[PDB]
Amino acid sequence: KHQPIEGFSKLSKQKKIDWLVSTYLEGNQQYTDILQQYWNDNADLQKLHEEFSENTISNFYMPYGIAPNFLIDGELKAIPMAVEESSVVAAASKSAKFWLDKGGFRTTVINEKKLGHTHFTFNGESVKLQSFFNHILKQRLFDDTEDITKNMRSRGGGILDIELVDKTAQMQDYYQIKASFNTKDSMGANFINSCLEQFGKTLKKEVELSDKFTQEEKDSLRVIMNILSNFTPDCIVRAEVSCKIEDLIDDSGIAPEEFAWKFKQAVNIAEIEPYRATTHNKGIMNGVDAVVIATGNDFRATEACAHTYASKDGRYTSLTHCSTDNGIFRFWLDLPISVGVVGGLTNLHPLVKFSLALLGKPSATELMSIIAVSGLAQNFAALRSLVTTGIQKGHMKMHLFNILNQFGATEAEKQHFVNYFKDKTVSHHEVIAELEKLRNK
Amino acid sequence: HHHHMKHQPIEGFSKLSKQKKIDWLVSTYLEGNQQYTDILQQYWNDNADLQKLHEEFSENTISNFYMPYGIAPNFLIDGELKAIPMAVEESSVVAAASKSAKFWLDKGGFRTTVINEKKLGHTHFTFNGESVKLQSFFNHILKQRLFDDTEDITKNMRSRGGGILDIELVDKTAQMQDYYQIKASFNTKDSMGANFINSCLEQFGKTLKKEVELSDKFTQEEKDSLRVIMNILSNFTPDCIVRAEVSCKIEDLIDDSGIAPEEFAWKFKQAVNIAEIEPYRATTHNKGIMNGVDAVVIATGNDFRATEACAHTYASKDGRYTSLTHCSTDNGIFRFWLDLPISVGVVGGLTNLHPLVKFSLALLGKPSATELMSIIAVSGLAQNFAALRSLVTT
């Protein structure tokens, strides 16, 4: 019978905690100490870290790690990573080391197109709305946003294009004003939503003022919502590694052609089996999200975007692909991702500042490259590990059953050898010596 | 690299002490400016043993990245009033959670139904012989042997009421030549289950290869063709899934904007329907759900890459990417629900050593894993409700 707390957010941090610990933790001061042991000693810094979210009562430590020696487009970077899962940072470092002398990582930033929509309904003829949009309203939508977009346009960005989309086949009377945006180094959410909110104002007002619509048709115009889309398939970058198959050298002594083919097979499984692609893509995001967090960006957005992209052709599939044509190994990731490097409240987080300074003050597109590299290297590490374990183990077992089949061993004899070599290693001499003992008493 | 030469690779980075890692990093990339060293060190805990503890979760740890740790109080969940811990960096997420809790507190609260707890994993392998011969061997001999050879591995889990639920042979040769799967389903009780599942699959791989090698049903050439590609769990668990739901009479949907309650319910359903039929909205819409899910996932030491991958795969499982929540306004009743596939643990994770994770679990009343599933689904539903309540009353 806990009682609800009124006015919780107005309470001081200390009174929030006293109530919390009394109500749910039996007044045990040890839970209070656990909250306070993560507080920063410095008053201003602690206050700063209580202004990103709301009702903050402590700091959740996420490990801040470094994976060094990433050769990215000819430059050697150390990548900061904030992630709680073990082996993620070590795998990143191991992939960077692997590719350091095999061409490193190369990226192509394809496009930086972000999207938003005014969703609305309208009961009149679609073609009258289209005609009005094409000849009048579209220009008026740019005009009424000139003040909103002045700063961004002086930075090189702005509204790239505006479209009317007839969605009436999906939902009765449903239309969109669909716009694309360049927000430069900003994540862009406030800029986009501000444009979209003015779009809805201009749409409703211009339709009401036009002689082309009946008053019934005007009254039917209703904006549902003005909101950006986190699906940005044209804000996207390719990260890629490539070398000659013969140069895929691993200290595990595995043949490079065998490794190349088994690696490609692991990628193909994720391309055709959705239950594998989910885990495979999750591995990519281990790398992506660790850098998204370290640079103060929104990983729900990068997750929602990447996994939507993974299903965009009608089947949930792998975000990475691989070819082994003509003696060349290629492995690449097309990662749609929207990030910012200025203008966010989280750009005030000092470790976000550290991350951006560490990476060389990257532009948004340069950070897109860095994050896509981190995802590619993480996926590479997982698959390289999964395929080279299967080569290490099967080498001794396949050696054994071929000797036994060359010697025509019975199934009972084959059984006895499985027991005998459970802990022992498989030598060509030892197998034959033991078979000689068994058959000749 | 403006004014110095090209950076040189560091050898033996992980064997450097923490301070030596930092010194190289700041000398190489930050011009030896001690202000950047100070930024790293100001987040170290005063207690040396606690600091070292937080340097053993990941690798190459040189500082602590603060994520805010917040409370959203007054969540009425299946008849109990919970304060939900939330670790998230984005503004308004925690406040929106509190506002949704407040709205539903006197309107029935949140009801959950944990539907199933089935987790999955696969032995992926190739085999060049006749599929029917592999299937017949599996059905009559191998499947039982796969259970037998994991008895020692599953003994601890079975005494907790879990274990391997079923094992199937899947023919994927239409998708890829000679490709097959041993597909297994698992109950891991209060564990996330990763290490338990992967241990079983690795034993499947060994038993599969061994039993085929020993069988007289196959030629030696067919035996040599059997190659295990990988033994790995799947983060897509559509049958480890909970519904969270709110419902009340439409006349009770009273909002401070003065919008009529029937108008609010209709505009709200409209906003949901648009996410159901427009993928570009569904992505953002589901993102809002994950704002709430991920904040509790982090606060309880769980893996949010896994929950993100699972939920967004689920969102496309019928051929189009669509909303994870749904809404009805039939017969004067407002209904709004979320079917969230989610796999989490409340024990046994390296992160249940994180004292704030222990705090979250104690705050929530030491929930079981299915009770945590419910709490997280409520948090997703409440976040989506808050987002859509704002978008239609603005």
Image: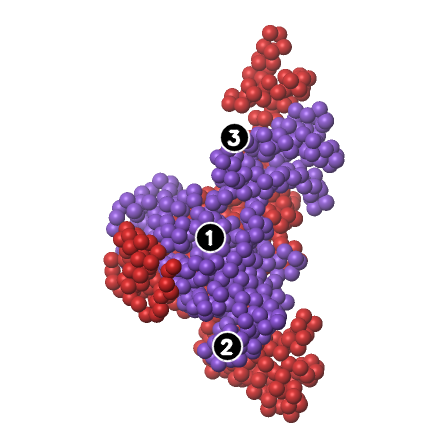
Chain colours: A red, B purple
Q: Are marks 3 and 1 on the same chain?
A: yes
The answer to which quarter of the image holds residue B93 is: bottom left
The chain that hosts pointer 1 is: B
Q: Nearer the viewer, residue A374 or B61?
A: B61
Q: Residue at 50% across / 48% down in the picture?
A: A378
Amino acid type, callout 1: Leu
Mark number, residue B152:
3
The chain that hosts pointer 3 is: B
Q: Position of residue B12 (x, y in %)?
A: 38, 40
- Which numbered disc, 1 or 2, marks the residue that appears first in the sequence? 1
Amino acid type, callout 3: Asp
Element assignment for label 3:
helix
- The crowding category of the residue bearing disc 1, from other C-alpha atoms within 10 Å (few below 14, some 14 to 19, many at least 20), is many
Residue designated by label 2:
B393
Q: CA distance from mark 1 to mark 2?
A: 32 Å
Mark number, residue B372:
1
Q: Residue at 51% across / 33% down in the picture?
A: B155
Element assignment for label 1:
helix
Q: Position of residue A407 (x, y in %)?
A: 66, 16
Amino acid type, callout 2: Thr
* Residue A45 sits above or below residue A243 on the image: below
